[PDB]
Length: 287
Ligand SMILES: [Zn+2]
Ligand SMILES: [Zn+2]
Image (cartoon, rainbow, N blue to C red; front, side):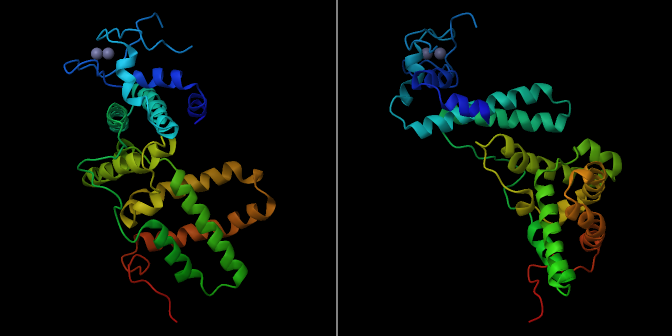
């Protein structure tokens, strides 16, 4: 997000050079080049410099940008930075499933710069939302269902803990399907791999690469994903508390220690219990 700020502050000539790298040549009706390649060994390139690949000037790769607005140039530059970022991540990524998603998104964004379009993810994985009621609604229903009768102070503390839990879920990294496979039944794995891919494309990667449409984990998923992940999230949360507790202000420290474990235990019952009412779209409280 800081390399983004820096490139968006450059003179327009330099911005066009950066974009020319990812832009189609229109020197003539037959040139099929998809990007200007600087002929110099690796201050703005002159528009007359000839592409290494196709020998047509930079001008002919960026002429479509001559009259576009400043904000549209900056949107495109954002995609360039995300393309650079995804490219690094693809090469660095050990996990197959993750690497393939990063590579799909890399190609998607590169193609959008080439076509001056807006990215949208597409494939057999479907599009959001994935399940209703979603996690955010389930958790709201849970707080009403179990805690409505508490005194207003204790009730506020549960609400605050619910908001913290939802914020955690929205930034927490899911297990890879390979990790999930090591603790689960083999037939559960294919369904988790679809949800993990959805999660990466719609939720997690867009947090780092904001040219992609961004959806909250807790808004597009529901009980099924929550059943897959919750026991690990819970373990990770309680462990993180053990590590960080003493950096919290004492009021928060005490409240987490004495109310959060039970909140999580009680939510676990509603997540996995066949008989829970909080996952019905019709959920309401008595008058
Ligand atoms: Zn050309
Ligand atoms: Zn070219």
